[PDB]
Structures are given as structure tokens and as C-alpha cells.
Length: 503
Ligand SMILES: [Mg+2]
Image (cartoon, rainbow, N blue to C red):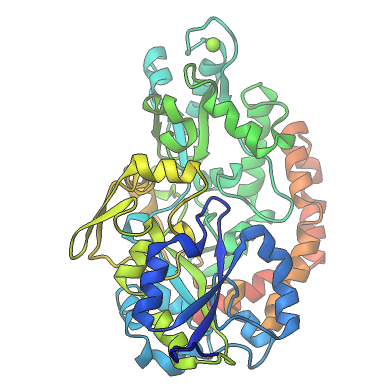
């Protein structure tokens, strides 16, 4: 557990994206080792490789000293005595204390109801504080056709019929896809889900992560499932009207993500798609980006602009970034390494790569990204850091120039500030620190068991209703069936955890 020079050896498991450079080639990782005065043995695992390797490792009983995006806190309860309770070590983690002070939601994410800290959250910076979900529309097409951004479901339908029939890309072909939507996944609502139209009805979604991807929401302090809501039924009928009218592709429900995205990107010369949910004009439309803007979501019938909401997610904080083995050979070195990961120097470098590579430090808290370089490195599968898999935090005092992914986010998020102000982030949104990873293992187990029954046929039935109709007839039996297999139990369990963390 010790070098020849007597430096402590620290094993560190680290989850990676496939497009990333190896830890051994990252200068910041060597700097970190030198600052810690230890030897780091990196164990690099991709998102997909880890999914197979994980439970085998916990069953094994043999975990790395420091673990980056390896485990969540509930696992410390599933395998007693495996993980260090970091709440007893905060004096050795001044950078973590600083993180908790500036971002109290990260403290709450990191601390369970017993006050223990088994897995510390991470943050990507205030530039990512808004939602990752947006609704994008071809503004050039609207201009060309002499139409306004629609503000109701009826106006939206009229705009889509105009996209369908008036050839707004000018090529003479009836090739326009008025609105394109992602297929449903079997077990959760996805990023950019067509169910983002729930916000039209006054129900706040949070599809970046957490509870609302299983169909839960809150209003006035009471947790509900939208799976059995009139609102969910109205969204599905509205989609059926659109699909039935040829305004969304017939084959949407079976179309793979790659083909779906290629629809929007087209050939980079002729725009094909009028409306999608997505990140940004640039991310979703590439070279065609100048034709597109983000729009506020249209209101559903009976729903006032004041009552119309937008997705309540934040892209900044992420739970379960850092965990430390209770059996760490060199515990003090482990803590020293973890504290350094949460310093600005190493948090920024984890995020955007080593200084001098694709990012330069221009001041004490100021950095400039060289975008050509970052894109080239990414293309070559040599991204110089951990990017969104950073375990650390970008402090508010840091100003980063040239993070295009952040800059585009900032611009589209301006569009949603009004609608997002229309809900209470506590009473009308189940906060991100209320998640299955912050519960008793017995409660998590119930929720997972129920989820397998709830999402046995729900997405399939939802897709079929959207495509083929028939919801009115089948709705009552569908709801009773969901309630009979544990939906109301799940709702009650989420209510309890919501109240524990919130009330
Ligand atoms: Mg055309």
C-alpha cells in the first residue's frame, strides 16, 4: 500500500465516457498525484462496462479506495461497513464544505435523513443551473409563412398544418416533418420526452434526472402520479390528433434515437423538421441552427399563461459523485485526494481538460476554452477530461469563456425564465435531492419492484393510444390496473420522502 519512497498508494475507480483520453495521459491527473504526494492507481471503467462490473464488485466486497461516479449512498446501506461516512471527516474536506455552503442543494443531495454522507454530489457550474429540456421551432419557417410562435395547443396545431402543406423549406417537396418526437423507453420518461407537453397542462416535469422520469410530480405540497392524471390523458389525445393528421411521423414509436436525430440534422443544407424537444438549435440542428429558436411551451385548453409551467430540472448538480472505501489502506491520503478533487484547480481541469491543452487559465478564477481544439480532441476520442463525469464542483466565482455547450444553454434558458417562475420549486416540484438513492434500501426495493409492474405495459399502451387512439374507452380500466399493482403505494412512499426532506 506504499511506494519505495514511502508515498501512500491510492486506488481510484473512475467512470469514463468512451470519447475520453486515458487518465495516464491527462496532465492534471499527474499534477493531482504530485499535490497529494501519493501514487494513484486508476481503474477506468466506461458507463456500459461498469453496469456489468458493478454488482459483481459489491458482492466481491473489494472496492477501490476512492470511487468516482461508482456508487450511490443506498449501497452503503445495502452493504454495511463498506463505505466511509464522510460526515465524520468534513474537517479534512474544506473544499466540500465550501461546495455545501454555496450550493445548499448539493449538501442535501449528499446527506441522507440519518445525517450520513456516503456519496458526495458534484456540480458543473452555474452556467448549467437551468433545465436541459427545451422546445425548439423553425423560426425562419414561421417568418416565411407569416406566422407567429404559437401560444396554445390550437395555434400549435395550425402552425404544424402550415409546415405540413405550405412547403416552408421551398424545395417543392412535401418533405417537412412538422413536429418530430422521440420513441418512448420502456422503463422511464427520457430526455426530450414527448411528455414535456405535460408542462402545457400546468404539471411541472423534471426529466433531466430523478423522480419525474418515473411519472411522479407535486403540486401544492402533494405528490401525485401523472400516469393516471386527466392531464396525461389530454396530452395523449392531443398527440393522437397530431399523428392522425400526419403532423408527426407515423413510425415515431419505433424509430431508433440515431435515425430520429438524423431527421433533424438532414444534410446540413435543407431543414426538414419544424418542432422538436432538445438541448439547443446548435446541438439539434448543427449547420441549420440559425433557422431555429427555443419557444415557451404553448398552453393547454383551460390553462392560463400564468398557470403554464416549464420543466424544473437543473443541469448543474448531480448526485453520487464521490465515495470512499471504509477499508481504504491509506484513509488520510484518500481524504486528501478527495478534497483536492473539489478544489477549483482540479474541478475545472476535470471538466475541460488540463491547463495549456484546450483550456487556458487567464486569471485567478478565469478560463478560456479553445473550441477548435476541444472539438478536435473529442472527435479523436481524446477528450482531455471527465466532462460531465467530473467529481468536484465549479464555484460561482469561476468565469469560463468558450464553453459552447454552456453558452447555448444560457441563451435557450432565457426563453423559459417566465414559465419556470410560475411554479414553487419546493411545493410544485419534487426536489432533486429526493431520489431513490437517498432512501432506505427497503423503500428503494419497493419502488423498483413496483416500477417493474408499472412500466410493464404503460409505455406500450401510451404509444398505442398516441398512434391508434382508443384512450377514452380504455382509460378507467388502465388506471385501476395501475393502482392495483402498487402505483398508489409508490405515490405514498415518494410523499413520505418528499416530506422528510422538505417539510
Ligand atoms: Mg419542402
